[PDB]
Length: 294
Ligand SMILES: CO[C@@H]([C@H](O)CC(=O)[C@@H](C)[C@@H](O)CC[C@@H](C)[C@@H]1O[C@]2(CC[C@@H](C)[C@H](CC[C@H](C)C(C)=O)O2)CC[C@@H]1C)[C@H](OC(=O)C[C@@H](O)/C(C(=O)O)=C(\C)C(=O)O)C(C)C
Ligand SMILES: [Cl-]
Ligand SMILES: [Mn+2]
Ligand SMILES: [Mn+2]
Ligand code: NA
Image (cartoon, rainbow, N blue to C red; front, side):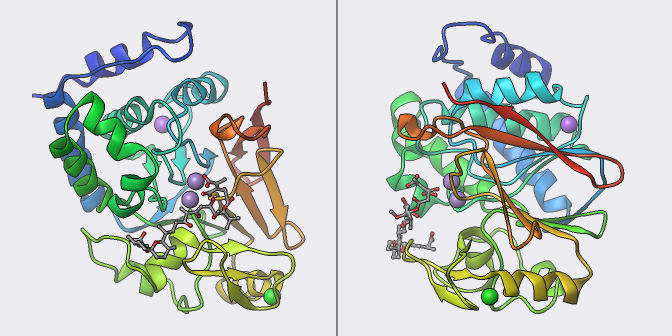
């Protein structure tokens, strides 16, 4: 019923247009993308087990033309495998185009293209920070709820070749075993506290020893020894996460045991940050492709 290639073609047609040109799919098409992608997300584990090589991207926040640039630089799917770390919607001008292209690629290439849940893939949050408004304006609120129902099924973490632990936010003081992640049932909203919350919301902090209060009003901060201890315990080499705007598009932490990726340059039109995508080669060596600030 869904003609994905037509949908993808229309989404990609605006490459080279005046940045800001909309792609307006039909309501029925977007419903289809939500429903089919939801089924795929539920059919795959909540803790993904992935293989290198792959490209890893952080926050997009509706910067659709920047998403197109990342694909231009990195290779359009399936030329490279992709893992996105969440925060597809809110803040930017073109969340709808952003999420529809991502969902279309998930349906087309479900074993080579992966999306994790960010703290913005949550009705409570995207009600406030732009996506609800974008949906109401360009479609209707019933379609917004369709998006929500899909977001509630996204996986929440990935491990690349048993060595790179990936999530949107960060560690949790409740995370003792990986089985705890695997046990989480879907669909689910993001709770106000606990493991799932923390994976989507926590931040590393150079000035915290152990676990600290998070100025976001949700979850915690964690220090370098929390990272060191976690990697040692679980025989991991790297934590890869997103969630925080960083000036270079990527930023290492805890003697390079953690990296933050943020893929939306000139974030919100308010920052002068680069956006970065991390290229992980066959041996897990990391390099970067970067959208420099304007
Ligand atoms: C100013 O506060 C920070 C951010 O700008 C804004 C945020 O982090 C917000 C998303 C966050 O504070 C909103 C939380 C708020 C909705 C919550 O609201 C409550 C009440 C309403 C309820 C529906 C909600 C449910 C929370 C629960 C976890 C769910 C279901 O999501 O809980 C209570 C607890 C909490 C205050 C700021 O963070 C940054 O600057 C990082 C940057 O990357 C960023 C970002 O949001 O990540 C920016 C610049 C941005 O876009 O604001 C940092 C200095 C602490
Ligand atoms: Cl610490
Ligand atoms: Mn986030
Ligand atoms: Mn974000
Ligand atoms: Na791909």
